[PDB]
Image 1 (cartoon, rainbow, N blue to C red):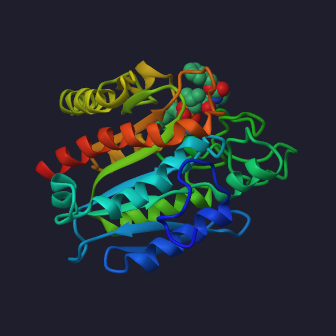
Image 2: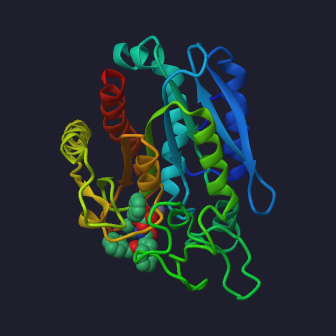
Amino acid sequence: ARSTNTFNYATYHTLDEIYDFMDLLVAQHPELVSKLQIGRSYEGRPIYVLKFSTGGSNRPAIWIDLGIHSREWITQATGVWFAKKFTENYGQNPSFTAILDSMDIFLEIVTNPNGFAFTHSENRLWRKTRSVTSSSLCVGVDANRNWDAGFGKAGASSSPCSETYHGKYANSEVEVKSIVDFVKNHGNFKAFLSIHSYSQLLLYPYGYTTQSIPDKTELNQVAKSAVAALKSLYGTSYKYGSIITTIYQASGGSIDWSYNQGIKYSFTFELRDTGRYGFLLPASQIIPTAQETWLGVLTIMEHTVNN
Ligand SMILES: CC(C)[C@H](NC(=O)[C@H](Cc1ccccc1)NC(=O)OCc1ccccc1)P(=O)(O)O[C@@H](Cc1ccccc1)C(=O)O
Ligand SMILES: [Zn+2]
């Protein structure tokens, strides 16, 4: 913590700790990474995105966000390891070097900071944002039911008290609108990855309809390859397939929106485990989870570079 080299990647961190880490990675790798503020949360916290870039102007780009659901702590812990990994492998890893020599990567480690801080202070199992519905005593909106793709349809709830409550209208949550404005404005995103836990699944569109996506054949083959690369390290098994078919029906999910904006490689990872620890995954599993997930993410980015 006097350098990202001495930061402890094998434990779970607080919001102050992860925000300070982003400042330190940018100070140590000024030619590769920068910190962008893309918005403010409902209670006033900055929403930051790390940009990894070799140069250029508006290059094709890859989006990755983690922590949209705050109790899924392995996802923010995996994102901190990804960020260091990126600065360790550029130059060393030949395909990763080749991706970053043609494209940029945007990494949002804490997509829901109010929920995150709330999981450290009052409820470890908090999922939603902290929007206050003054109609109810129930707080927050499920930010992964707030996107404008099948919004309001089966797979989300109209009660503010539901864990799956969609909000009063699409993009009502500022932490969803912040991504939406930034991605649309950028205009050159090629892949959109949103990481969750748990279940060990690789998911692609759609969640709000049983109809197949036009590109189902291609995405199924990328998912198949990505899941094989991941299992190569420690034998971890993943299942993959469309959201509605593989976990359950869900409307207003971010991957369905991005795919409908024309971003073809739209995938959600559900990380470890399959329920034995669930959201409370032991810290001794952070680095093995991050390492095998990298192999899965790298496979998809390779495919995106190549076509
Ligand atoms: C446990 C894991 C499946 C996470 N889900 C959750 O945390 C859910 C939320 C919920 C509550 C009530 C009713 C329905 C759903 N709650 C929950 O308790 O999960 C139980 C469960 C696990 C496995 C299978 C089936 C059910 P996750 O948030 O990662 O799942 C994604 C799936 C998804 C990804 C991408 C797009 C849409 C949906 C999501 O629900 O937003
Ligand atoms: Zn989730």
